[PDB]
Amino acid sequence: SGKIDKILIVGGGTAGWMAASYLGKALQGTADITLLQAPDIPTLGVGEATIPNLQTAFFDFLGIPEDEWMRECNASYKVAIKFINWRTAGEGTSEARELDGGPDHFYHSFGLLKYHEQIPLSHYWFDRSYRGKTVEPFDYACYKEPVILDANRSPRRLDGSKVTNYAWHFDAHLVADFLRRFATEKLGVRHVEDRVEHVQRDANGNIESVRTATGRVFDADLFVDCSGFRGLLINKAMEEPFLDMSDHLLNDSAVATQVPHDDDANGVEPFTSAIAMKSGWTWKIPMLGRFGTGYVYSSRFATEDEAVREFCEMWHLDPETQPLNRIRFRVGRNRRAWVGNCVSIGTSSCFVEPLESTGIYFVYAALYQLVKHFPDKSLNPVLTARFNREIETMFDDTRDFIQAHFYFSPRTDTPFWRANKELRLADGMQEKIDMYRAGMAINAPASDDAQLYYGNFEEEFRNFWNNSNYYCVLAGLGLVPDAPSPRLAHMPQATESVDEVFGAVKDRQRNLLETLPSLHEFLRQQHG
Amino acid sequence: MSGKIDKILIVGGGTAGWMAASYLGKALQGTADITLLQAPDIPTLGVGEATIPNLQTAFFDFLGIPEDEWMRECNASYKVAIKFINWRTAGEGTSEARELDGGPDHFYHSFGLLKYHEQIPLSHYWFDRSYRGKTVEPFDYACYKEPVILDANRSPRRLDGSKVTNYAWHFDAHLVADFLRRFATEKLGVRHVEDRVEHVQRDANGNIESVRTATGRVFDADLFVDCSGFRGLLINKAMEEPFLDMSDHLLNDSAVATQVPHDDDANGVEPFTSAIAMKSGWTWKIPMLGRFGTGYVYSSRFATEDEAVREFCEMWHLDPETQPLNRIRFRVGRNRRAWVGNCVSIGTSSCFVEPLESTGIYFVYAALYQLVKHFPDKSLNPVLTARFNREIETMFDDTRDFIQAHFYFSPRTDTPFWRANKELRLADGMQEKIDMYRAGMAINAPASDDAQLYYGNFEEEFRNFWNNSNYYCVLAGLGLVPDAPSPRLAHMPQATESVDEVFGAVKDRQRNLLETLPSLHEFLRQQ
Ligand SMILES: Cc1cc2nc3c(=O)[nH]c(=O)nc-3n(C[C@H](O)[C@H](O)[C@H](O)COP(=O)(O)OP(=O)(O)OC[C@H]3O[C@@H](n4cnc5c(N)ncnc54)[C@H](O)[C@@H]3O)c2cc1C
Ligand SMILES: [Cl-]
């Protein structure tokens, strides 16, 4: 019996310091926290893209205003993910190829999808498209974002007012540093820079203590494994099996670097770019004066050298001198994220390519669940089982959504793209696709007020990938319902007034394209 | 083949039938021809129906009917909660609460919303204090302002009309059915045909082609809605869809009921439904205007119809030999599938569970909302049908489990009935909720403690129908509490300290409303 008195976090990367901060804040003065991390070879800041609830679910919980952390972490703004060349054959290039009279790209914005008589706008759009009343792409018809993004507009007016939902772009290293200073200076977390050499377990199989290379021994009531892909505690010591899911996702590697950028001459893109390649895709994460970029590929379809070549050749970099990070990652999740008195947080727990910026999200989402299911020293099995259930559905739902990006691409030009169609969608994903094809909304939000949504975590965790997200991706790639939603034929009054809505977004976007200052313009002011 | 549905035939003209005619008529106004076939049934006494808040927001508001309009025509009263009497003490079936630990044996399950404190339901702070011996006050009186004002039969609205608490209604279903029949036929163009179904003609695909009536008339349609009640004329008889008897979770399958005249001037009116525990079941009391409906829901396995009639009549001091009574044998459970082919079952033809938590009418409009949401065209995409069936299935089973818990967790062991309930098994899904409750976790806590956003948005409420508040009201009320306080609270000394004024605010609302609110009767008079 008794509450948890000591917590030991193993690992000092982004996950480790977010854990120290979140737990240090949530348990302020009722638990002694120590973070243990081995100083080793650091990597290039290849950039990180995020989602809106980073501020409401994480930084707001710590009591850190947006302005404070993003200025210290030299962050930029992200309004969407621009998918480039996912529908056309060809080599890996930063320039969109031509498709049906236009550039091959489509957006997945954080922007809200307007309802109309209890029905998502997406459904009205497809009805008109299917009956030939429109030729306009889904994103440009239902969202105001596409047009102001094509013009690299800021998501905020010079006076600071927000005109749309947005997330952030930043170097993970700087954020980890910011959080380390915060956790140690303001939350009392003890930082020990040493390397774990031996983990001692008791007869119940729980971790008793960890011994470092210098011979120091640390004990705790609860151990948080933030050791990364190695899973030092969860996989190695506790022997919990990692479940590989490469049967759903072929990508398992990446070659990444940071590239200098002339913002003055080219402005700053208010979005992350996902550029389709021959054996994967490449991310582009604009930051201040540079952009992080990385080629995510499948080791089964391209050798590291081929990836290095393809990657450097698209950014016109020199393979021989360009500093490059060659990464190999495991895809999937542990059979159980929390076993005994060991909780895995971060890549030690689960991982999927950054195609939808879920990496950091998985960390604070898991920390939120750990606090919600926080135990005492008796370690009630029920709290552990529930936490584990929340993690598996969180991961598996994203895994499926991401697989859909590859499964439904029309490309058949390379072994990679053709191989993605050979895979099997999880039963849950197949059911969602069937629903989509039948004209149904997928996980429509009970309400269409982003505020409530992006402001209330419980509500967002339960409706993470909603109808808007699915339409952007599926419709963007070319997968559309078999026929218009049956209910529409019974709503003449609705399908008539819907035009007011479509016109409203057209005006909305015409006005923003004229009154909004470029992202660069805003960033200058924003950043001293 | 893919033109929209053009014709719909509703078989059955009771409450479910006219609710369906009204909802579909409103939803598909002018794009579908609706006909309802209704045959004369032997009249029954209006024994009363209790409801929940979303009846107005999810049903009448959808139809565009103001609360005052249907209430006045259906002579309805107000319901603020369900008051459970004598569920924790041994004894005969009586209308008087027995004594338990210094007070009457009752607890309320009201519509009030549990206030969150530092992101944690007030229920957790209450149990923490109770467990540590800091309080001995019951969960409902400590966390809700309703109990105090209900003990005084207060109105949910001030004389000026201002609402002070969430509430639902009490009324004679027959009157609501008539109100809707008139609304649908007069305002929505629904065609009413008084005839009896004699034969249902199906095609080689197993779908219903048409139904032939006793007069020889043949009615064809694209979609058929079975609102024929327990006999499930279409869904069970014609479509042969199996019915899942769930008597392994619910022992009650019968009822004896009547309507009793009441002098509201002399006794006032109770703003709540009473659920009175009996020896082999429980009895409802639904206050209406100048009378109250009441019925003893019992298990034929533990009481004969005669014994049920005697226990029921004696409790109300009525003559068993001459009191007009409605003897009913329920069909408890649900169809394997609510919608099969082009036949959708709505109402008791679809599913039924004893009215212990007032879900009868709710199941009807909730299903109609789900039907429109998954509305098909002539191709009848099987995915719409499957998704519909999953929604209905979970809606029912979750309620089945919730209701079973009322009996499973009662501390009574005085009769074979109460003892047998403890011998049944809880469904795995329910056992998991109990494991969570015992571990100090909230059970399906609402995304937010905003009652309006809750009872105002159906999609929101449907998904979180039985929430943490509902579970604590019933479980803690019966006496089942967590094994220990939520471990999180030990790490929140500031919160467990500042919550003392959240409980104080409740006490202030209890005291102020008790001193300023008129009686339910007073408010009813002025209306
Ligand atoms: C004892 C009892 C207590 C209840 N208490 C509550 C409560 O407190 N609160 C609450 O919300 N709900 C309560 N309910 C549920 C409520 O009564 C029902 O939800 C509602 O009234 C709908 O009944 P129904 O239309 O499904 O079936 P029925 O009333 O059985 O209707 C059958 C209909 O089908 C028709 N029919 C049958 N065969 C044919 C044929 N061959 N041709 C033409 N027509 C045919 C009949 O004419 C009739 O109109 C209670 C139910 C019972 C039995
Ligand atoms: Cl009001």
Image (cartoon, coloured by chain):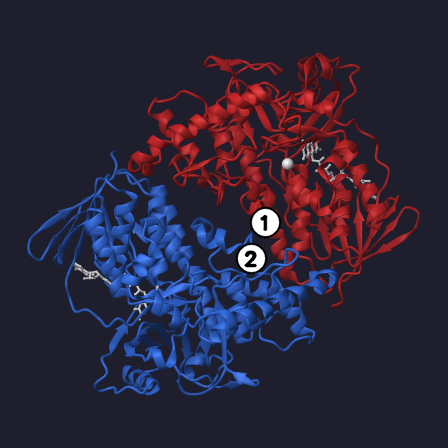
Chain colours: A blue, B red
- The answer to whether A119 is drawn above or below residue A221 in the figure is below
Which quadrant of the picture is home to ligand 1? top right
Which one is in front, B140 or B153? B153
Q: Quadrant of residue A307?
A: bottom left
Asked which secondary structure carries label 2, the reply is loop
Provide residue B172's location: percent of width, then percent of height: 75, 30
Determine which of the numbered discs, if any, sits on residue B459 in the image.
1
Q: Amino acid at mark 1?
A: Glu
Type of amino acid under label 2? Ala
**Residues under numbered marks 1 and 2 in contact, where contact means CB atoms less than 8 Å apart:** yes
As measured in the structure, the alpha-carbon distance from the residue carrying label 1 to the one carrying label 2 is: 9 Å
**Residue at disc 1, secondary structure:** helix
Q: Image quadrant of residue B282?
A: top right
Residue that appears at 80% across and 60% down = B6
Q: Quadrant of residue A198?
A: bottom left
In this picture, residue B56 sits left or right of residue A520: right
Depth order, front residue of B171/B12: B171
Label 2 chain ID: A
Residue that numbered label 2 is attached to: A444
| Whole-percent x, y for residue B342 in the image | 73, 57
Residue most extreme to the right: B215
Q: Residues within 10 Å of mark 2 (few under 14, many from 20)?
A: some
Task: Confirm whether residue B478 shows in the render.
Answer: no
Tell me the chain of label 1. B
- B346 and B198: which is toward the camera: B346
The picture places residue B310, in percent across and down from the top left corner, at 69, 16
Q: Residue at x 39, y 46 (%)?
A: A386
